[PDB]
Image: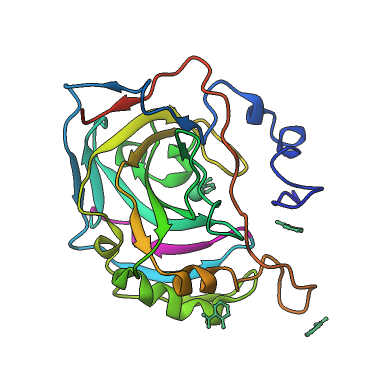
Amino acid sequence: HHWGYGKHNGPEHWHKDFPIAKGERQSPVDIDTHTAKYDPSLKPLSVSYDQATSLRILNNGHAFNVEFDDSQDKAVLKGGPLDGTYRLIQFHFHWGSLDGQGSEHTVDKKKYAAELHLVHWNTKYGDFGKAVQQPDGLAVLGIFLKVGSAKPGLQKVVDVLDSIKTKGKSADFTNFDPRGLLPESLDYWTYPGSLTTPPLLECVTWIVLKEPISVSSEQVLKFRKLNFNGEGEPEELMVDNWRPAQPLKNRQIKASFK
Ligand SMILES: O=C(O)c1ccccc1O
Ligand SMILES: O=C(O)c1ccccc1O
Ligand SMILES: O=C(O)c1ccccc1O
Ligand SMILES: O=C(O)c1ccccc1O
Ligand SMILES: [Zn+2]
């Protein structure tokens, strides 16, 4: 599988190897804020990250993942639209070549400079690989990034990127606190969707926070120095690693707030 974000292997091509790309609950989507419905029965999100154990950071040739110990209930998401306990396995970002693009979800067609995805799996399915085969297997917390003031809690991530410049490189990344990436408010939109990269499985309850976080231009510039290619291969900057909005089809986006 040689999928990517280039002209010859990008999102418009993914359906040839992954036919679910044209399915009924693909992500991301545009969030029409005037069409989303407030649902008063939606509960507040419960983000319990105090015992989180980060292990490693990896450049996988499409983004970088910060990975966590998901062998115990150390960092979990529950409540909101979710039934059960969802364990944090990794987070990653999508970002642009310019500050006016980079997010996967859009809000009233507005694009943010980047988007953070905190990926969690439903513990009733035992492991991530089983969870991705279920319609309620994953819960992804999505957070928009806008360029402005620096985010202090992001800087530890930025400072390690030089050690994982190319595809396949990893580095130890212990004692990172993902709570430093969250905005003040946990108000959210939610809808059923999919992974946004191949295999594009329709297994995600998306929880997209309304409040973006601010990062500095210097922080996002360091993301843009990463490479899609392996060491010794022709340099292709890791930028614009986002899938565009897909048709909503027979879905409704719900809001936790009025
Ligand atoms: O593999 C990619 O994601 C890619 C992206 C941009 C340009 C060329 C590429 O191969
Ligand atoms: O110093 C950086 O911020 C950096 C980031 C990504 C890749 C190579 C780098 O030197
Ligand atoms: O978010 C995704 O698209 C994804 C895809 C494959 C594996 C883990 C993931 O989070
Ligand atoms: O291994 C290579 O082919 C190579 C090519 C360009 C620069 C550094 C390298 O190691
Ligand atoms: Zn993602």
Q: Position of residue 125 (x, y in %)?
A: 37, 37
In the rendered image, residue 25 lying in the magenta stretch gets the answer no
* Quadrant where ligand 1 appears: bottom right
Q: Residue at x 58, y 59 (%)?
A: 98
> Magenta residues?
62-73
Most distant residue in the top direction: 250
Q: Is residue 244 in view? A: yes
Q: Position of residue 67 (x, y in %)?
A: 41, 63
The C terminus: image quadrant? top left
The colour scheme is rainbow
Q: How many marks?
A: 0
Vertical order, 211 against 109 (above or below): below
Q: Residue at x 75, y 73 (%)?
A: 235
Q: Position of residue 11 (x, y in %)?
A: 69, 41
In-front residue for pair 255/99: 99
Residue 141 placement, left or right of 47: right
In-front residue for pair 242/82: 242
Vertical order, 71 against 37 (above or below): below
Q: Position of residue 115 (x, y in %)?
A: 45, 52
In-front residue for pair 94/217: 217
In the rendered image, residue 65 lying in the magenta stretch gets the answer yes
Q: Residue at x 43, y 46 (%)?
A: 128
Residue 48 placement, left or right of 36: left
Q: Is residue 134 in view? A: no
Residue 239 placement, left or right of 205: right
